[PDB]
Length: 202
Length: 147
Length: 248
Image 1 (tube, each protein chain N blue to C red):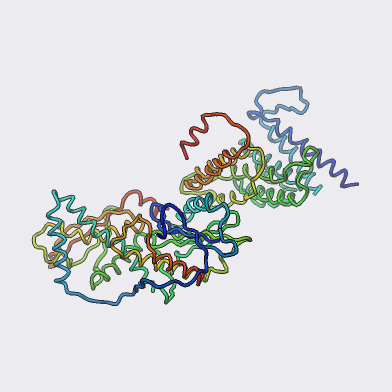
Image 2: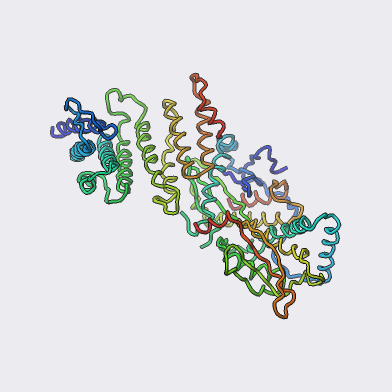
């Protein structure tokens, strides 16, 4: 009963100091876990989404929604704790060019979820509006056997909801290019839409 | 009087407040009913126009007095997801946000910390208002102590 | 006095040039009258009107507020209308600011950026003329204010100003500057005749639409709605209101 959408509550300033009900904290406090306890919950994502899905494509694009609802949380956290609350800072750049947020995702999102920075970030040289991001080892899909890459898409929805809430409407698609002795190399191609494309030209 | 609002992605509001001095207790006399949301929704657009400008009309988070209309200035803050913290200031004479410009930058950062703290609840979707009794005390103690 | 004869010439000159400025119609094509203040020139009605307005504005700037600002606006309108005809009045029209740059300050030679500077100085001269009695004529001696006739100058200033912004990637005038230079009139707007107040909000909606500001449009149509509701007289149905309610 604070913001109803029926009205704007009109309340006078400089009232009393009220009681304190719930107080949280926001710094990182780098607390670890075991990769088995992650991979068990990832296979319990997939062991229900195999059950309540009829074809492949809607399984793809509702495994992606779980990653969407981690990406739109994580975008507001990572810049805000990288620019550093009551230890008052000077805030971050709020990046607004497509190869200034790709450097941020490439060097900080993958260094946040995973221990290492992702290795390469490859422009599609022979055309425009495709932007590859690769690694050498997807450490969440690494217990899936076979070759079909539907089980990839929980990480790629983390990418897509990172950009869709950043003002950059895109669409990701993952593929597998087994280059060299890295048999699981697993490119994602970020593929921005047409209606964004004029705006960074002007 | 002061009007403060958090405007969402589709321009749908998620927090909506006014707070004002006790000299004029019924604040914003015949503007709060009929101009005060219109000037907010009308002057979202220059804040939206300023989100893709590198230099204004090397921080790009705080924005100054972006509009001045009948002697009411508004101030803005474009967060990382794009929720914009626009706030209308009203007075008797020509109000100055320049006396609080060093101050209330740490009012926008200290409400953006509260928005990040209420984003992390996984039950909280986007495009629904903040029905939080904790949020009101957490914003009005900040409004009382730091104006 | 010398100021009395200068006031007589200041009353004479601008009106003596204004009807010859108003003696142009479809660039004066085959209208040979009795040749008493109707020359019917081929392509020099703008040139003769510009020479008349140049002499009149020179005499009024030598007699230097309200009629001075109207004289400077008349010289600006004569230069703009002479440039609007594709003619040879370019160097003569640019050098025709001999008293306009003495009382005003044009100091340019571009496509109406000189007229932008002259229009800003004309609004500054009308703002200096606001520091006077509210109405200086005979029938305008107990009128509203100078606030009902400054507004007709700056709304046609905006109407002439925003057309320089054609949408493309060259912008002749940055997009924010006429958005700034239309918000200067927060005059009270409380009382005047209503059919000025429909027209100012309608063209302020149209300048916001051509700039591409799709919520300031909703603001000025809401002001149009509030001004239409509270009028004390009675109005009738017209199909303009149909499409007005449809676009809002």
